[PDB]
Length: 136
Image 1 (cartoon, rainbow, N blue to C red):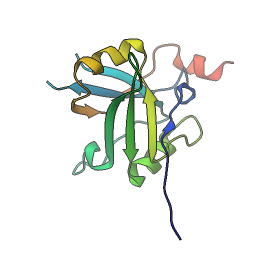
Image 2: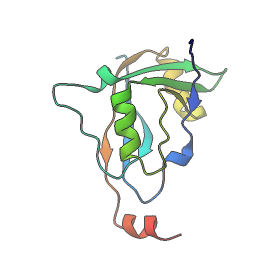
Image 3: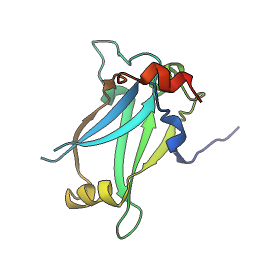
């Protein structure tokens, strides 16, 4: 019959040291703000015709007098894509959120929560990556 939802935190568990990582870069209207988003096995490339906004809506809101969160909504194609690239076991829901720290929040607050643009961005591992991931 009838259905509706909720915004799950995407916790720090999904970033796993040793592995490559996707970096959410937020450029405030008008010194980006960089959040490691999700540790991945292979880089994210999208259909070249397409672009991230097609698949990924985000929104920055305060959570209190000092802290701020980033909410977002992930169309299924990206959701499925992200889950397959993900090291941590399929952690991406359609409606999720993310906690900036007292530090990160501060910028967002000053920009009046107003996003000019954003993108994801594949970043490689450093010289001890393979050794880090495989030990433990």
